[PDB]
Image (cartoon, rainbow, N blue to C red; front, side):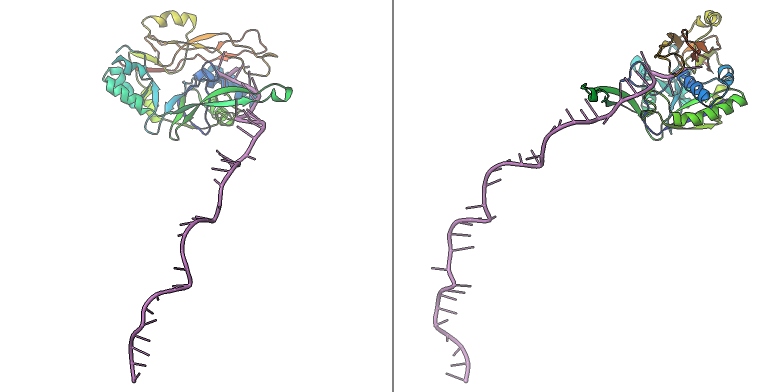
Length: 295
RNA sequence: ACGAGAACAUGCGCGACAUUCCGAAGAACGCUGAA
């Protein structure tokens, strides 16, 4: 049951990539899954549905004009083609067939208006009272245009879909990304049946494109890599919880194929464990959502 | 179990100092009009 989940952001979001100063306009499926797990644990729900039947996608840019999917890594002005990152759903088939030209790719890049990124310079006055000093730091945020929003597609049974609806409503108050609970990431989310995507997903093409940041199991990896065009993205971070350890602990470093990576042989994903001797297992979504296309 | 959590762009600071609404300037010029 693939359900579109559109997110409208009221306040700017941080979405850090490596540092607090930087910012991204989207987040990986794992970052969303980790937020969904944290929420389910707060609301005292069973994690079996999320860990066994929920399939999600990286949040993708959406505009009133169009919904943007990630640019497939398919061999085809090379600058114009490399600058392009997201292609509207209507132009995805044209891009796959090679019917797109460099000027058309430039127009597609200009078409997206997800938002306007910025850097907010904050200060910490915690040490001023102890003969210390104010400490400047920078938070990179991204402000969506009013029509613009981030959407994700969630697939699963009816039970996990309803659980997702509950977690999503709680999540909007919780927020997403970094510096949430410090002014950022408040969003309001709608869950609906989308005719566009379900029709798009009902295609049996010769190539498979990874909607979500995903990694195959070892046995899956050996068949999948042959003839694959892909971009290994390091997935790293600290553990966010009150019960994992007394102090803040980094997760084990993970590498996942990025969204838009094209694999000839489809691989199902796996919820990996990036924990290192903690009081609970830190789950890292790496399951795979596939858009089959014809090239 | 969201490159995450905690974190006041904050503290101090007179839109202020100097600067004549002055200078020149006769209320007086022609003497006529009507019956």
